[PDB]
Image (cartoon, rainbow over all chains, first blue to last red; front, side):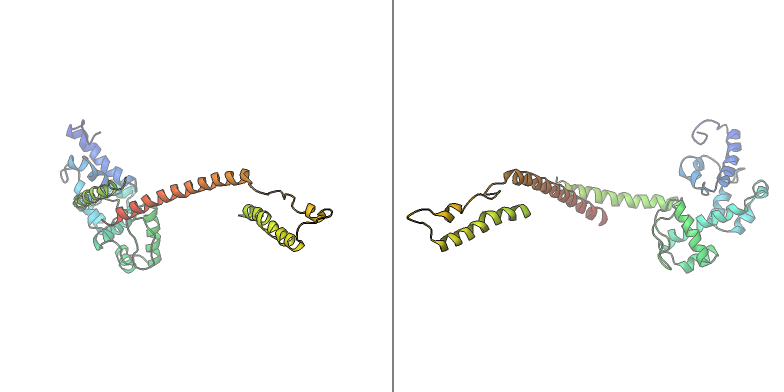
Length: 183
Length: 88
């Protein structure tokens, strides 16, 4: 509702925009920037001007404790954001490797990316599977985590949709022609 | 199948041996009966036509064939849908 219309009135928007950054860090279910990206909010609130909004988006991409340690701020690190950074690291890297590589990542790579043991990577994979950010049976050393792709990917999900539309239009019309000779 | 085999062993198999025996005996006695000729042939419990079991059987096999047909019709279209979605 705030991201749609009313309280714009930018002073009212600023105070809840700062609260929205806190709300994203407050629940580790809130991904990182994904909820803001998904509809009007990122297309309504300034990135750098006062909000500090794109800083979180930069920390998410550059994927490290060092980026949070550079970019964090007194209110959230006092309580504080130490555990949640590891939960963030687990979701972002596991998605990013599989998204780029492209889609059947080696165990050996994943240990280097997550910076933890083999059995620790398998433990991270279990709750990645419980989250359903990845979702099929896990093989031993290669073909480690596959499918779902639920997370944000901006233009790399928009371009995928444009490719899927082309695929859907060919497939649905062609299969309708076959089933219209067989009904 | 057991019901048909039971009637066949009464219809054919008993009668075949009775004619086998009656042809050996030869089969007409002119001064007086015909004692064992009089004894021969008396109906077993199926002499023919156990239709009450048979017709009810056939209606059930027709119901079974309808279940095979509906299962086949489900399989025809499931195979088509499975092939159609994958290859594009």
